[PDB]
Length: 507
Ligand SMILES: [Ag+]
Ligand SMILES: [Ag+]
Ligand SMILES: [Cu+2]
Ligand SMILES: [Cu+2]
Ligand SMILES: [Cu+2]
Ligand SMILES: [Cu+2]
View 1 (tube, rainbow, N blue to C red):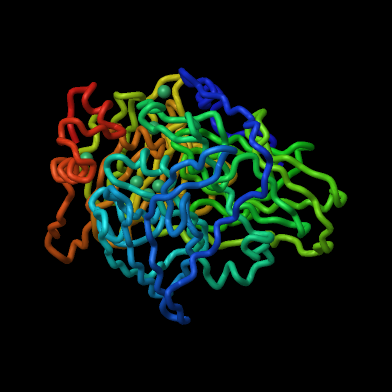
View 2: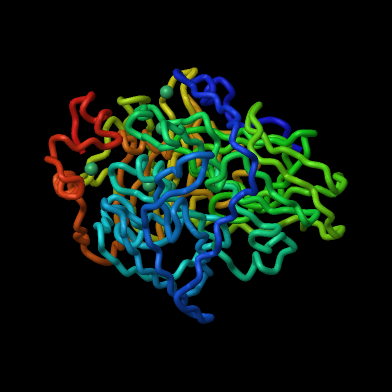
């Protein structure tokens, strides 16, 4: 039973300069929103068709005025999208927002830079784009979010994020809760700051070192409760915050068992009383409420702040038990002739950088052949006290081999796409790209992302000549935004610009 957070306590966000503590809202407690499942336009055993529509609207979050929000196929966040390993997936990306966006499938092993939906995949106002892909990767929880470069931070803040569930045959065979919305629920962890008339104001809250508001928002709900009607419940934790770290535990120190990470089931279940998640990380846990009587309640906390109340209703006894082993991890081979790649994250605030530079949308920072796993050493250069930087790579699911030459954390033996790197620490990852393209790698503190803590790698088939890709440029991006907002390029405000400008550089 893991009873403490794994990360280095001195580097926790709560020691940040200008740390924003969470405060319990006075808003009335209400049922946790569970995003509906997006209904396919059509579906067979072999093909599924979806239309995913970015849209602007309004959402009742606090008593009083509705908060203006953005969402996918709804006003805030999104309907949950289900993908299936081996199923040919066809998606119409529709943008009905007043500004351009991008549709990034975080953790999905798809081609880049277009299907990947990163910096180079704009979808302009009024436009529809079509993509198709077949996922060949294990069952897991992924997510969809906006990824214009910039500002990913602003678009996520507005509400553009949705859970993506990947199903496969192996997971389906297992005794896990799986009744979506009944005993299997998203827990998208975010925070916001509400201004006058219950509005969000990213610009007013902007901080190049990471934006955090004092009001926790879970699945777009303030002060939620969940009605438990089964002994066991599956929680799909997703850290969807711009910066905040979640340090999760129950009252009574009720234990819970992690069965999944970002990219796969864990090889074996891992039991915990206290679990920490950095930005973009996912943890699927099973909670067993068998020791509670009907009518009782149990609250989930982050640090000393209540997040989510579980109300215990009558439930049937559950006699099932987790197998000793959930999933077999097959590590790809590493060609000994390959170098160990060294990636160095540095800086904070406006001076964030990777390998001595801020992102430049037309600069390739690295290449790697497809189909060849390589060791990546990833270092967080910050001296103590520092912050934990969650490092993320597009177009892959990696394995974690070591932290400072020692074992990874107990819940890091499955496939992952995002890893918290502590000040002074070097983590060794095993990284392979199955598909050619251009893929970002960056910190997932989203203000750091926007502020230039990002690079891109061109993965290539060595049997073919170098491919040419149409990369977005910053002049094109700013022209578009200018037209869209009815202003001149020079008066455009974007999250991340301040970091570039203050360091005298440009994207
Ligand atoms: Ag900092
Ligand atoms: Ag740019
Ligand atoms: Cu992401
Ligand atoms: Cu990503
Ligand atoms: Cu960072
Ligand atoms: Cu990214």
